[PDB]
Image (tube, rainbow over all chains, first blue to last red; front, side, top):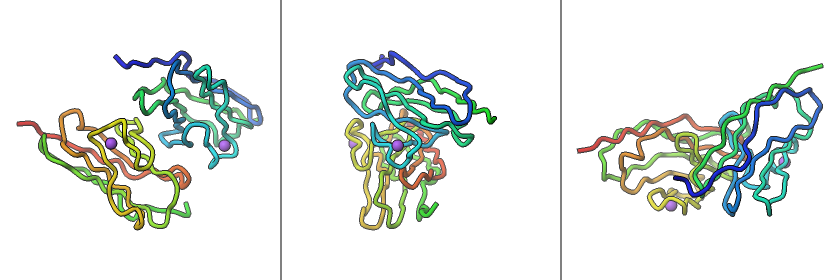
Length: 102
Length: 101
Ligand code: NA
Ligand code: NA
């Protein structure tokens, strides 16, 4: 089987516009590339999501954490997100973020 | 999108054992390009070192990021797309049909 497994995977969430949200992703003992995918499109490579001011990879990389923080949820963030590892060739379960607008 | 594909991959039928190239080009784009196979990214840019069977080829000066499958096998029958991170564009998906003797 895949040498690697996820220790944490992102979960579906309902959030309010303007609220931060952290989607969890962790892979123990894994020192390769991790990508976050939003509706099929990669947001960046590793911690470099510099094309998206609204998205930040956080968590303790020493703990194998690659959490996606959406700093201020807006309706455009209502999407399906997944975490995947290139060298490990594994994909997390997909997580739907529901954004509700005040 | 300030950027667009000059070439995108097309569906292709190939026999097991033969190489096959999937075209992808984005003129004047100096950001990241990824190849995606059945929803999974194969590498970043020219670094597809996790897969000895897949090489990115083509003239990078002309913005080409062609995927060369060196020796098609049954496990390579899949849907492929190329996509650009900073440009935030995805190509059309290309289905590679691999036929076996
Ligand atoms: Na960012
Ligand atoms: Na390779």
